[PDB]
Image (cartoon, coloured by chain):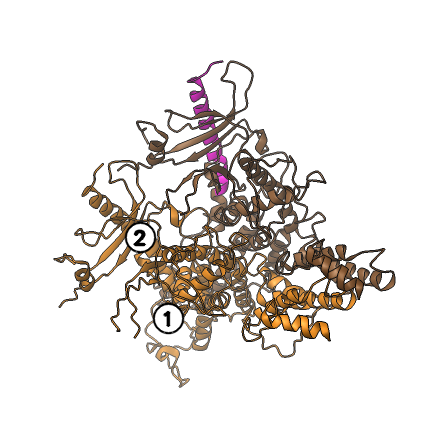
Chain colours: A brown, B orange
Amino acid sequence: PMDDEQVLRHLDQLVNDALDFNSSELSKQRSEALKYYFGEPFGNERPGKSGIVSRDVQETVDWIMPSLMKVFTSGGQVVKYEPDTAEDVEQAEQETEYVNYLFMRKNEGFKVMFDWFQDTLMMKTGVVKVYVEEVLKPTFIRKDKKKREIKVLCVKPENFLVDRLATCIDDARFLCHREKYTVSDLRLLGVPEDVIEEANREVWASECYTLLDVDGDGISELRRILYVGDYIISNEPWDCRPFADLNAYRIAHKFHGMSVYDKIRDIQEIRSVLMRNIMDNIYRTNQGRSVVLDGQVNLEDLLTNEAAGIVRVKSMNSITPLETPQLSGEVYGMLDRLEADRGKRTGITDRTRGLDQNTLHSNQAAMSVNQLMTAAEQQIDLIARMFAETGVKRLFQLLHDHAIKYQNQEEVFQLRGKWVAVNPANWRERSDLTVTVGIGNMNKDQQMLHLMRIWEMAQAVVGGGGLGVLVSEQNLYNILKEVTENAGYKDPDRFWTNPNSPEALQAKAIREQKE
Amino acid sequence: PMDDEQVLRHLDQLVNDALDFNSSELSKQRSEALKYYFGEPFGNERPGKSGIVSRDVQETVDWIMPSLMKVFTSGGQVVKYEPDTAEDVEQAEQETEYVNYLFMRKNEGFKVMFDWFQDTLMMKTGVVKVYVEEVLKPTFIRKDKKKREIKVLCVKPENFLVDRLATCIDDARFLCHREKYTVSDLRLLGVPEDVIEEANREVWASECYTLLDVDGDGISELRRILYVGDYIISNEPWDCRPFADLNAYRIAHKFHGMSVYDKIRDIQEIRSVLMRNIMDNIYRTNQGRSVVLDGQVNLEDLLTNEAAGIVRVKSMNSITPLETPQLSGEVYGMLDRLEADRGKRTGITDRTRGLDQNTLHSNQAAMSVNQLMTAAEQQIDLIARMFAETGVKRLFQLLHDHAIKYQNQEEVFQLRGKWVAVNPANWRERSDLTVTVGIGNMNKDQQMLHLMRIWEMAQAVVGGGGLGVLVSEQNLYNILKEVTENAGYKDPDRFWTNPNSPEALQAKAIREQKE
């Protein structure tokens, strides 16, 4: 109750414990993963022997990434809102397009997404941070005064201290983010002096989000602490934690899931060892092994690698050359099956290429039954599913950060017009069904089903019954509209519009009826 | 506060530190990469033995380049602007076409692009510089006076000193560019004397971009310093750093990403060693290995390579010829799989040739499912995506440097007419979606989907319902306009225009109605 200095030492103790545990465990694991990625020697390499390391996780990551970026960083259809039925187009589409328009094309593009995906695929956990800034450009043309802009950035997860007893973002009692916050930022804040650590002195700082009770009452809400160096700090009650913390594999109830390294390290070790053995056997067979006596053949055949062929002995005549058998063809098959198993584990793409010109293509029905059930239920779809289910948290965080206060700014969603984004509703609910393992039909198959099935059905309806009783031009407009949606030229470039418009009235009730 | 000379020594210290660190680390890495590229010996070659070096990064780079040139140096559709809806054609198309027309066909062509791609694939980072000139030709025909022309150029990245704590272009506190700026340029500037270092004395100069506080206040904005030789300098507050610093692989939060060499050096080493071993084994088997005594067979078989067949000994009769086994066909498989793995890493194009004449071609739907999902999610697409998202910064830099003040010059975009380029808007937003991993359908697939699908859809609409209520002639003109867009004869060579034009009035209300 009424704590002002003991909170500083308590936070310092918590930060020190987090540093020790996180550093030891996660730094060890991530250093192992990074050394595995860059083909660093494992430590068992022998002097005077090749240190051949078969990079195996590099290709795995480089083939996981393009699928995820194709399925995510293409359009703003990743997440919907689905509000109450009558009021949907008023805000749900507007708010979804707004959060898409500010996450993409407004916040460093998808570069943050690339760094986030590297963090979640390499450091076993990828997390970003959402904060605000202020634009005060005194240009008296584009006088954008008092622009409290929202920015999202990756946090270099080595500086993402958090207690282990969370198992979720909204379950931790303490989160620490280590930043620099150089002397320029401190001077802007207003502190008069410096700490132990030219104006810029590369000082270190930290930010703490934790729930406590400093008002002499029960446990209060979240508090943000600008604990830099045990000095003038910024303590303030907060509302929500702006973090996303992917894990990319969703292990049982522990916070940090495994990474690609954690499940392909054995494959990489086996492949590297076998490659070293193969090339060592080749080198030994070419160089040759022989037993020589002491006192004769002192020249050790001049390393036996001299391009002369003359050995010379002294006086001894025998020399015992031992034979090292050459490895059979089974090892080639072992490498082939090792690569096949590595692919089967996560990168089920086979050779990641389609340069088989002799092969042909044939479809029986439903577009080769959905390309053989999406290449037999690719794990990539599940990975994207959970990636989207966790980015729902980021999208909600940005929606809240706009609903508090951003600006009177507008969008370009197929037509001009968007009011101030400070009075939407949160809707407390999001949906990402249109991406992945759910209904989530990929555009190339969703459009095939849609076009073929529904179009032939509609043609049969028009020919047989009539567009009056059954589907009319109003719904035929949608039949074209999602087709153009899959084509990408949705509203303005190919109108087809005719919902109920003044031009539609002339087109329909003048020439089509009085003809 | 009020610093006029300590800034010189501070900048000198920063430049010296950057020189030391950048030189050591990056110069070592780039020298290794360059030696690997030109097939230079690795240092482990033995005297009197073949120094065969199997070049592997050469073909990789020579296959990466053409895809980049095809996807970038073809048309001005790489980057759009997407402004507010109502005012789009007024400036967005105009400004986009202007920046394309000034970067291309006006500034050295794409040679800058070629050098940029070599720099970003060779030295782990490719960066260009954008500056302004002043052409004052007194040709009193083409009186081109006050030609504040903007020019871009690659900067030979060995002269791009920058601190390591940036991790981004607009995050470094200090950027240094080393130039020559010979005595002619110094005399033009107005300095009276020379430095330690014929009129031309190949003098050395440097340009510094860094934020400081020299006005006795808080840390100010960026300053440009003409720090040449610790002499008369040109200090001035600046606005934006004109660099783009491609990295081509987007490693985790460090400035310099890895290059092709950093991931194919192991493959090159393995292939070179294995080829050397193979040819050494062949040469040894042809030459042969035999053991001879001392004092007899002193002629060492005349190096055993004489085309005579007569050996001669002395008086002994034994001779011990040892047998070196010949390499089996398993090494054939090792070479094949090594080439396959080198391709699968980045150069996923298999032999880059389609002279398999016995092969055929067949399609089930969606044009062989989009050439099998773009050859199974080509890494080239992701590389082009990141290049576009990084060159967006360069395009914005050019737009700013032109919108500040350039000239009253015009364009040839499908028609004459373009006003002065000093009053556009920056729009603070760019889009490169029409190229790459996003919706971004490559022209051959976009055109197939668009043309085919939309064409049977429109024909069915016209036959069944009618062009009146549904899609009209205006939207059919858009259909044909994008069809020709995919072909390159867009507006004038095949008009089809009829949007609403003086000829369109007679086309509609005279022939089509009174027939």
> First in sequence: mark 1 or mark 2?
1
Left or right: residue B279 compared with residue A330: left
Foreground of the two, A227 or A41:
A227
Queried whether the magenta region covers residue A13, the answer comes back as yes
Q: Are marks 1 and 2 on the same chain?
A: yes
Residue at image coords 76%, 62%? A510
Q: Look at mark 2 in the image and give the residue it sits on.
A: B161
Position of residue B191 measured from the top left corner of the image (x, y, whole percent)? 15, 57
Residue at image coords 51%, 13%? A216
Query: Could you tell me which chain the residue with mark 1 belongs to?
Result: B
Q: Is residue B79 visible?
A: no
**Kind of residue at disc 1:** Lys
Range of magenta residues: A1-30
Vertical position of residue B14 compared to residue A222: above or below? below
- Mark 1 or 2, closer to the camera: 2
Residue at image coords 31%, 29%? A194
Vertical position of residue B395 compared to residue B464: above or below? above
Q: Is residue A144 visible?
A: yes
Q: Look at mark 1 in the image and give the residue it sits on.
A: B49
Secondary structure character of the magenta stretch overall: helix
Vertical position of residue A463 compared to residue A373: above or below? below
Q: Secondary structure at mark 2?
A: loop
Q: Secondary structure at mark 1?
A: loop
In the orientation shown, which residue stands out farthest toward the right?
A: A465
Foreground of the two, B219 or B414:
B414
Position of residue A331 measured from the top left corner of the image (x, y, whole percent)? 59, 61
